[PDB]
Amino acid sequence: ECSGNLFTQRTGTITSPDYPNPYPKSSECSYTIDLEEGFMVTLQFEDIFDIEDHPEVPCPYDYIKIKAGSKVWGPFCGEKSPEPISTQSHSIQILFRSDNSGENRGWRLSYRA
Ligand SMILES: [Ca+2]
Image (cartoon, rainbow, N blue to C red; front, side):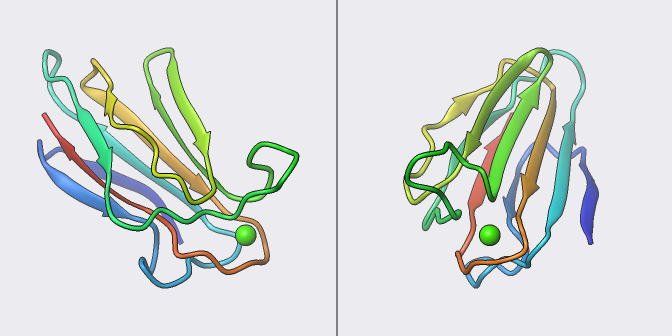
């Protein structure tokens, strides 16, 4: 269980459960950053980024996705660290799902506003 996190602080670091050890099977995590209008959240992935992937289909197993207003980033998976995101928003949703198998270390991000 890792759904429904809510952060109103302007700074923080967020990780997949158990990072940098493997994240649980069948994860459904969500993290909302809820700041006053006018703040603009910037996000960066840090350290090891390792989400299961597939060699032909884009992120069909596990992934992180970020939403702010109508804008979506991701899904992201694999071993490449996503590029930094300047959301231009005060209200951000970070979603992570995993399927029922595999072994991958997960992700770490920091945010600021
Ligand atoms: Ca998996």
